[PDB]
Amino acid sequence: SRTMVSSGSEFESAVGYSRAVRIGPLVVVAGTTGSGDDIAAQTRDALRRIEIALGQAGATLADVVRTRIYVTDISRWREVGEVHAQAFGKIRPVTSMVEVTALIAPGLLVEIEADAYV
Amino acid sequence: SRTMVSSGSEFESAVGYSRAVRIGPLVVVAGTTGSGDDIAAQTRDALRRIEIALGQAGATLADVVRTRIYVTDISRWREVGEVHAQAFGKIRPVTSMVEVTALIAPGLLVEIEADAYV
Amino acid sequence: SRTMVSSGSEFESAVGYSRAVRIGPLVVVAGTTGSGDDIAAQTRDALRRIEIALGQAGATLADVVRTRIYVTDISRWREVGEVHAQAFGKIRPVTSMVEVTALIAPGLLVEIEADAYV
Image (cartoon, rainbow over all chains, first blue to last red; front, side, top):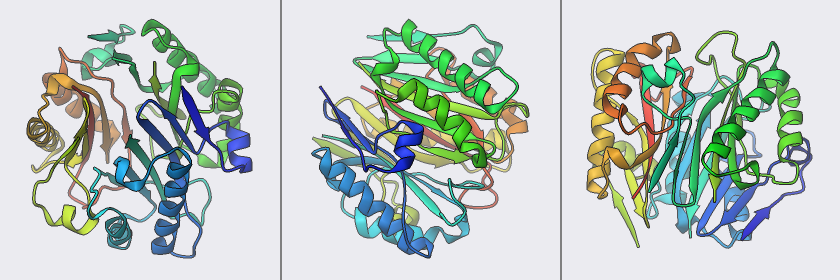
């Protein structure tokens, strides 16, 4: 039995995708970006939205087994890591962080995916 | 019990990988590129090949819970989204779309992965 | 019941993540880079570390269903493929290989993720 979470955004509309999908104990979360002027704020906001999507799929951050982080400037990995650490210091999912040339819009500095179990 | 799908390509040969693998209800699909001259045609063809690989693993597009899209020019996200939407408007897996510097060959404009359940 | 593997590195410290996590039959492995001067050596070393993390989570390379490979120069895909092939010629998980602008440090030429089942 499959459940899906939508945020009502046009982008989900134009591309045909969900914020989160749950089947069995698996919950997957879409690449998520954040509001905010700088990389730290955007990371916090991206993680807040992941939590919101998770919670609507009956999951919490404690269920997250993997995150994947795309940044436009990996030299700023520490600003991003600090926020990920404040969110996942106990939980400690696996992650990756790689630099990409661009995200969907030029002001967007970080995008985060998540996989959760349970 | 594990089943694997091969397309017989040299690349699978040189790198040692499968188009799709199924164990339990999980089916994972390799990064897939498409034939065609422009981003729309390549997206459609990449999705056709994903379907073919899925079907050989006993799965359909309706089982897909996640896609991940790499593009060489994210300013063309709409051409790609339209095709993803025509394929997944009802199903609505989660996705991500990020721009990369290059794919395996210079004429290749888009690559798509998929995860499916069931 | 969840188990996690740590390597004791500062980076896991700063970012708050695990080398590997297992729940149920799933084992996910973090993006992994390798020591060594050139792309071949770094790929071999990245795969050795994946194996080590897997083994500490009760898994082997034969359980791997997916790898994902980030390289800084995809024109060198053959050097990387040869090593992946020597590791996975029989097993044949699905993969993807894409070029990124940078990894976490400038001398790092390849990063590999893995998903395993069982």
